[PDB]
Image (cartoon, rainbow, N blue to C red; front, side):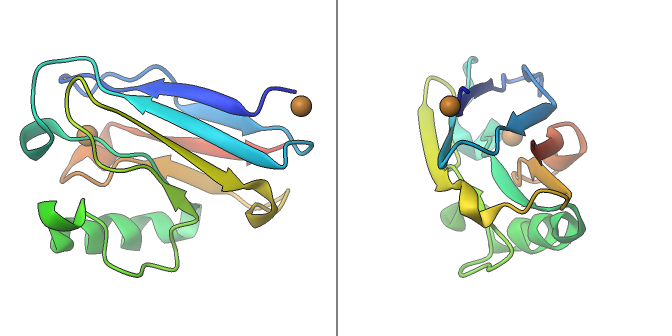
Length: 128
Ligand SMILES: [Cu+2]
Ligand SMILES: [Cu+2]
């Protein structure tokens, strides 16, 4: 099966997908984030951050607290299963992670931890 997905978010908080399926036969999985648009990362940055559903709230909240110079992620956050950098317009970042970190049956969410962006850019990731 395929083991990659392309994800983009613009200056308008508009993104291409709210649901990612990771096939169970993938050993690694890659997310390629891009940002169409004209605003820089300090004004309208986006990241892609993966945790269980239950951990999403805390990761988001602690991330906002940590600020731009930490890419809005609390340092050393063991709840983050994988994540891209925070990017701004015209930029691109890709993360490849080990699919052995995911357990069929558990509920995962992906999301942007830039302040407030969690409300509009988030989604489910499922291992099938
Ligand atoms: Cu395959
Ligand atoms: Cu964003």
